[PDB]
Image (cartoon, rainbow, N blue to C red; front, side, top):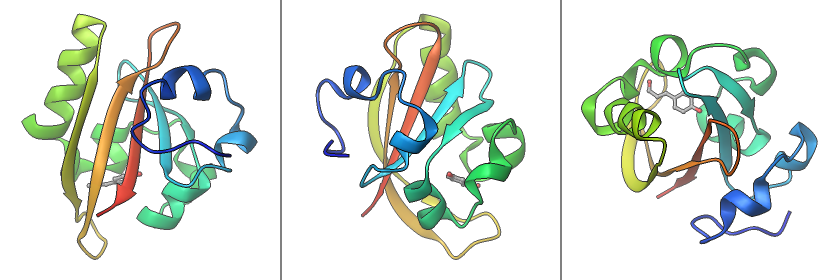
Amino acid sequence: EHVAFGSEDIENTLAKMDDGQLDGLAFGAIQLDGDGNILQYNAAEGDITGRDPKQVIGKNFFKDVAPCTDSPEFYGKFKEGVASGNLNTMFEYTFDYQHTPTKVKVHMKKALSGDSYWVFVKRV
Ligand SMILES: *C(=O)/C=C/c1ccc(O)cc1
């Protein structure tokens, strides 16, 4: 899939993509509901993080999968965006829960329709 991390219209290009199409991206992509439950999780993300994309679907990202992100700098920004119904933030972060510390660039952006939210990830 020919889409660049950080592109202005990423939410339109990815909108309603099925699981298989999302696996074609060059960067990690997760779709969350407004409570943080994982709706989609692509192959590129699993390669970065070690998680098995099939097993994490349905888990809560902040409470279960990614406690290192349960902080004002990541979860706090997410929940503020869900509450306001708009989110578009890019920042670096280190993943270090039961894995070798890995620094990444994160882009969180509200999905175009409904009340869903993207978390995009690439290595830095
Ligand atoms: C910290 O606990 C981070 C964990 C994590 C980040 C991203 C993922 O896709 C999975 C787990």
